[PDB]
Amino acid sequence: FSCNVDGGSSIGAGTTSVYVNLDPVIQPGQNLVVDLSQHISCWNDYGGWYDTDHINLVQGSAFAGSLQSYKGSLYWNNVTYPFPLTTNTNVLDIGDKTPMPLPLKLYITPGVVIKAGEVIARIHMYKIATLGSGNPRNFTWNIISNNSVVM
Ligand SMILES: O=[N+]([O-])c1ccccc1O[C@@H]1O[C@H](CO)[C@H](O)[C@H](O)[C@H]1O
């Protein structure tokens, strides 16, 4: 099982920065959207649904931190969860070699509120396959804005 960010080199585990362009202003009482399907994709390294991968997001995934005071929602594969995550999400099954953009969106409920270049969320993703032990692996996606977000 492998992923990449913005079509870059393959990733098999570990922590990766994911840079995102956000709305430069965050309106009071309105959600700021961080569409991660636009950046992260993963695939089965054989294809053909032979050793199918099973992917979920993990309890404890949260805002960073410093910025933990915020609340929000995390959309993952047909379900919208409160964020930070207090439980593991549903499982997404990956069996094609064609990359699948992750069905993942973060919603952030509100001078500069978000600083470009700082980690603003840490999303832990868990993989286990089907054959043998399943060869479980952990990924962490460190979400970083390319731009300031204000008021
Ligand atoms: O993870 N890999 O870098 C990798 C590259 C080529 C072939 C298998 C492979 O890993 C294998 O992939 C299969 C299907 O995705 C399962 O995830 C299995 O657990 C993994 O070891």
Image: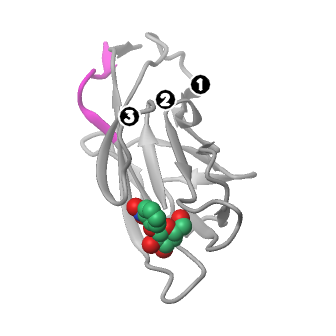
Q: Which residue has dot 3 on it?
A: 8
Q: Which residue has dot 1 on it?
A: 29
> Is 114 a magenta residue?
yes
N-term-proximal mark, 2 vs 3: 3
Number of the front mark, 1 or 3: 3
Q: Outermost residue toward the right?
A: 78
Residue drawn at x 65%, y 66% is 91
How many residues crowd around disc 1 within 10 Å: few (fewer than 14), some, or many (20 or more)?
A: few
Q: From which residue to which does the magenta span run?
A: 111-120
Percent coordinates x, y for residue 51 in the rendering: 61, 74
How many residues crowd around disc 3 within 10 Å: few (fewer than 14), some, or many (20 or more)?
A: few
> Is 140 a magenta residue?
no
Percent coordinates x, y for residue 101 in the rendering: 60, 40
Marks 2/1 in contact by CB < 8 Å: the verdict is: yes
Q: Residue flagged by tag 1: what amino acid is it?
A: Gly
The Cα–Cα distance between marks 2 and 1, rounded to whole angstroms, is 6 Å
N-term-proximal mark, 2 vs 1: 1
The Cα–Cα distance between marks 2 and 3, rounded to whole angstroms, is 32 Å
Percent coordinates x, y for residue 28 in the rendering: 54, 19
Q: Secondary structure at mark 3?
A: loop
- Asked if disc 1 is less than 8 Å from ligand 1, the answer is no
Image-quadrant location for residue 7: top left
Q: Is residue 83 above or below residue 28?
A: below
Q: Secondary structure at mark 1?
A: loop
Q: Residue flagged by tag 2: what amino acid is it?
A: Pro
